[PDB]
Length: 192
Length: 192
Ligand SMILES: [Cl-]
Ligand SMILES: [Cl-]
Image (cartoon, rainbow over the protein chains, first blue to last red):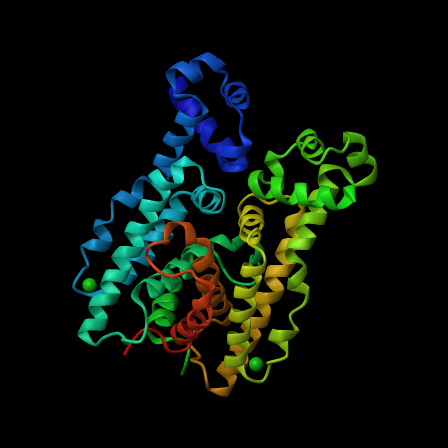
């Protein structure tokens, strides 16, 4: 059971202060574990951080709701948006770790974060590439940059929440309408 | 001169570890200043952090390159992209502070970060609103959510750089082409 309480405490301290702001003394104190339990049995600060980040990014190795729509690029893009919104609703901590690693990487960035993000961007880009070949999508746009644009739309909506509280709804009630809006912008733009 | 060296040291330590990961002892040690100089003359950890964040967000109070294009929504959107890219090229530290505050806010979030971001989003939304009234833009999309989408495109391109190194160019040589691509997606979508 002190394994579970350590995972909780590690997630909340590393989420707050990042890997570079947390000490093993703080982890032990917050969990009521000894520095020795932590170092010898739970992999130290580093082992706990790796375990926490692996849990944060676990869902990125499970892309079948998106991959399963291949053959219909619009359905792929829609599934990607729905999946991404779900991820954020289920895990309020994720953008803390995701942005902290992208802007102040640890050794876990190359091991866990970078391949997770790249796998998703690739998947989207492949679908865009297929749509371009088919003539559904315009051939003067670059598939990866286009994928990054879609990913940016949805991820910035959640990232900017605290600064935009009175400017738009962030209620989960409106998530399906957000998907409708971002699918429309990405595929058809804002032009009349 | 120890004022200048303190600002440098504060920017680099707060950029790395965030406000919540930096101690006044670390600041003094890194700058070769006493804890007393810092507390009594430079406003302590908090004063230094406020000064650093104010410098990080200073350019957000200077939006005339964007505002000056009002009357032509496309020119506003283009100017916004160009300005945002410039900001990131001139200040590699900015997304560290920007994401850290949005995900782990300090008292400086409400004072500095939130109004800076809101002022830009408002400006974009107003231009989109005008274009909708004029019939240039579709009336079934929400202006603020659309503004957030454009902001998300460009900000995610820089945010995701470390994870996408081999997937697309991030060379400043290609910044004008990026603007061309993101203007095209936002206004016309990816459809043929
Ligand atoms: Cl496909
Ligand atoms: Cl306008």
